[PDB]
Image (cartoon, rainbow over all chains, first blue to last red; front, side, top):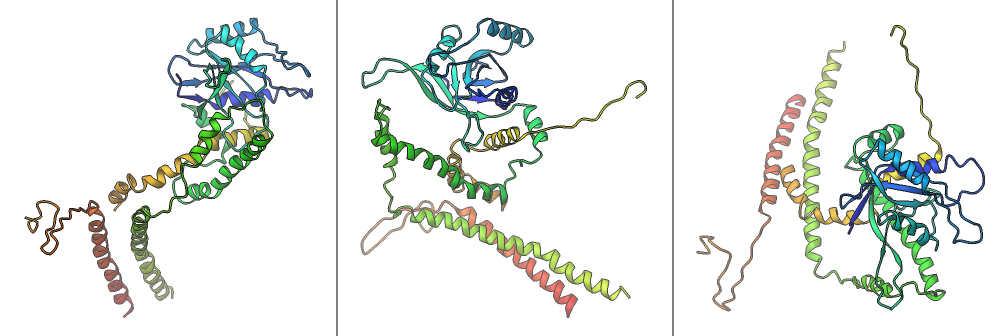
Length: 286
Length: 57
Length: 55
């Protein structure tokens, strides 16, 4: 149904507010906020959101506390001031997906339309993208397990339309723009290996752990496609790609001729002014 | 300015806004897995950029 | 007609083998060679200004 979503940083800075207005009480649980957006178009666009007092139990996980009057009053006043945005779903700040999320999401599945779920981290130490759109749809399983709520990952992007780019750029004054060239390219080409190294290294350890020490079926069926796609590149002998290395290396030669020739053109004004300026300033100095 | 003046304005930013918003904006200019759109340009150098290299020349 | 370059091909007498091939990237070596030839006059004129100002 929905291919991609658009999440503005305003809601995540509202999660920064979720971490600001705590008051140093010692709970810092998965505070659930009421996510708002535009479900009209096929693409999802989050503009702003708000929160609702949400408290769980220490031992029992099935305890969840929501509010209908606060949702209808905040949504009623927010719709009165801005009727272009309506309820879409919710989101929790907890890093782990608990079992009670089917009951928490089920309320906004009954009263509200199909709600999207977003799992983020309480500490911004994760290098990866903090936002993951998880659609709440029921899928048929091939093994015969009963139909249950399934959270499929929907791709997400963090973009701002008109003003939030200007506000973020003014508040930071440290981040740089695209700036194609040497630095913005070589930084990605340096740290990209760590950007994949922390992800893959962080995933395959618990993966290999759950291979031998795993039960409660984790959908082993998708592991066959996992190792299949991993074995779709069986160390090609590079025999056919030699001519492609001749093509890319020939373009490299083109960059060599462009650099040497163009820089040789740049040497004109320098290697002329260095003489005509020094000898004339010297002969005319005294 | 008569009977109508103004006041100075300063800002404030803690480490949670600095790292969450900074990494959020860098990620807003980066990719999902950060390895997706690299080979796109690495292999577009042979298909599309060649036109930009000929026009550049 | 191959000497007239109306299509891609080449004949043979000993074996009679027909080969058809083409070279699409023609606009690379032309612009590159023109940049080399045009830059030769740049470096030579630079050596004329410096050779004039020195000796």
